[PDB]
Image 1 (tube, each protein chain N blue to C red):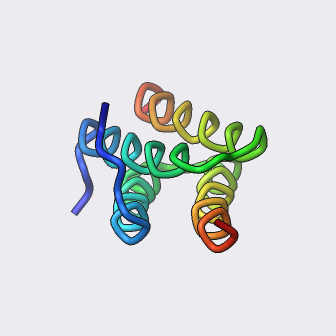
Image 2: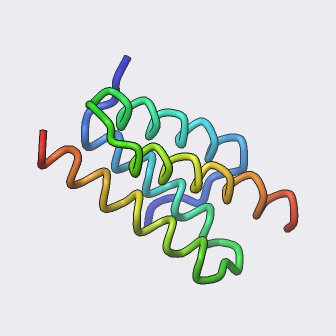
Length: 48
Length: 46
């Protein structure tokens, strides 16, 4: 029901998700989860 | 300037809508679910 963004929009939004999450004390598992999703966003796009 | 929890969930929603507009498999799917859990539970815990 929420909009489907373009790639650049999605990455802008993802930057804000990361800004939110890292505003809290963050364990290494959360950091890893951020870095994995960021990677998927770039590389799914690159391949698709 | 840090988003509110609601803005965070909105930006994440749109990030998810983007990723799911592609065929993704189970690995990428599990990465979505891991971060959606962190957003709610990091917030809840703090």
